Image 1 (cartoon, helix red, strand yellow):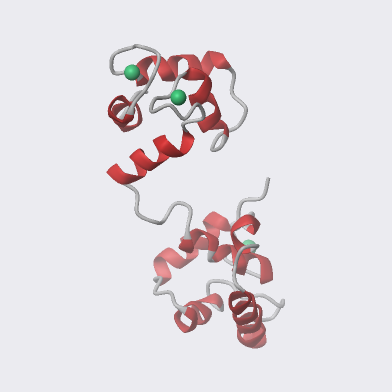
Image 2 (tube, helix red, strand yellow):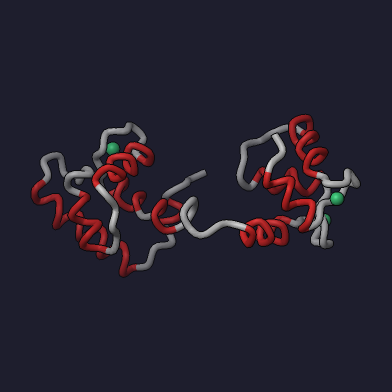
Length: 160
Ligand SMILES: [Ca+2]
Ligand SMILES: [Ca+2]
Ligand SMILES: [Ca+2]
């Protein structure tokens, strides 16, 4: 499915208008109708970002499907999807507990293999029970079939 568009499609009218407008105001010095790290650098400090010049080039090269440093009306709205949510917000001992009660398909306090297979599908491709079969085995601190908030803590802290 979509990755960035899904995060921008939720933006607020005040965001698209300010973004779509800023670009049309910062591209005035552009040449192909876009703003690369050289032109998008003035749009970030004006909006609400304090990225550096060394990381900037890396930010685009990572989200850019061609790794060039340029960003148009699309690459732009995509530069806020990675700087707002997804791989950025906090994530430590709390992110592990929430993910458990948020993926418990059986919703019974624990999770079995049939449930873990769905949790990875929400964040992984289509694997077979063969690969997800060893994940639940080593993820079980006591090898019982169900995984609670305690055993799950280790299963995610390290396994392969
Ligand atoms: Ca590009
Ligand atoms: Ca369960
Ligand atoms: Ca267990």
